[PDB]
Image (spheres, rainbow over the protein chains, first blue to last red):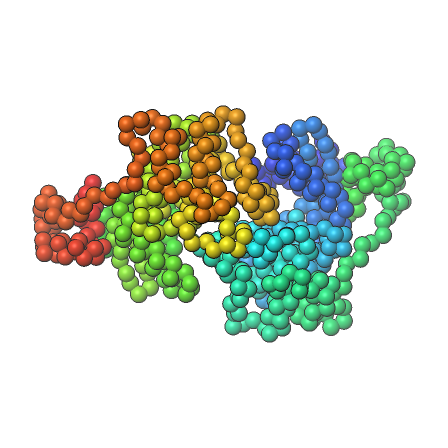
Length: 293
Length: 296
């Protein structure tokens, strides 16, 4: 629709770099063929959509428009033009702790924001953490991140799962490698269940102390992130601004500047209003959003 | 571009490297695996050595043959069978599912090969299809891991037995005939929930024979699973082999005295003496390699 599709940036669903016509703005459009999706995967797709709609945090990709046809679902979102953090590491060794922290602060914020809404990512990879033009985290190979309880036939519901995973993340962020590894599953399981991981000589005690806060075998012995947020390593170099849960900014559905512009385009205030209050994510809403730059 | 007796040709796998090469004195093609041991951490070294001990012993037309080991302090070299036709994985993604007649052909070799390993109390412990290669003649050669895991993994159960391999083989069959995995998910929890339940989708075109055989592999309770030797008697396995049933593989006795080759080797300047010693020795030095490679 409304969007001039530029190149492809992910295949086989496809993902297309596009420019929103009326605003000139760049968006990634995810194009999904529902007809190919088996029963179970469709539920997951729908669940995923419901979640995007509601997430609004600077470090989680923003959803801009959903366009639905019988065969195809299109998702228009924020383009992360910085690649994956995965790459960045393989590119540029380990991160120095100053930089790991910078990134890791945003990650922890994002996930904790999710948590505020009783949403569990349930599957943090680093195939999952993107970066934008300015090296900011944007959130959108899975085994090493699995929590113990997985391998134990334990329930796998909580936020505590995410916390564990973040532990893993931190470690690879600062070590350039996974804490728990193996040439296979049995081994990775024996290694994860033991919980012991190699401390690199260059690690700060502060860092190791924070690692301990995440990677705790017993699930319901794990900090909330809101606690973790108070951790000392997290807040080095922020002596005056400590990490706190992110607070959503208040809805602004009435910006006269854009409403103006949109009337110019032929939208009625009426609908602009309806679409936002509605959180419909129709073209009216996309347009309002994209004029938000 | 040298090492022992091998002209290294192209690279065929990176980041250890694996180089197609031509054994000079015989003209034969071999895949050389070059490993930098300095880079291997403690644990990984044990697994390498363990892996080497095993190769040296395996001798089955559908497991890659080990030809030579060349050890240096930093670098270990493993010279072996080159399977030119790539992975079965690929072949499927290339040419839909296999029809049963063909699934069976391949799957016979696979089950033979694993069972041969079992005779030797060796458990592959990690059958992928990233693991099953094909040679020039579409024969299986044995050398993405999660969907193959047996239940007991996710349950904290011990994970030692042959029974592990059997389950995996179940998975293999299924993908071999369906062109896809019996147990899937967008993630671990789901793949676990799916594997623990055991239920998998039956495709409309599947024979009842086939599904009967699948049931024989994929049984939740580990110590309720056939040996492969039982499985080998299965009806589906043996359709189209009414007169030759799959039985455990019997490897043929050693011949360290092939006059034809010993000859040619003397010609090259090896002493019978040493040819003899290397083989009895199961040294896997250049003398042995050459003997082996002359066996084509």
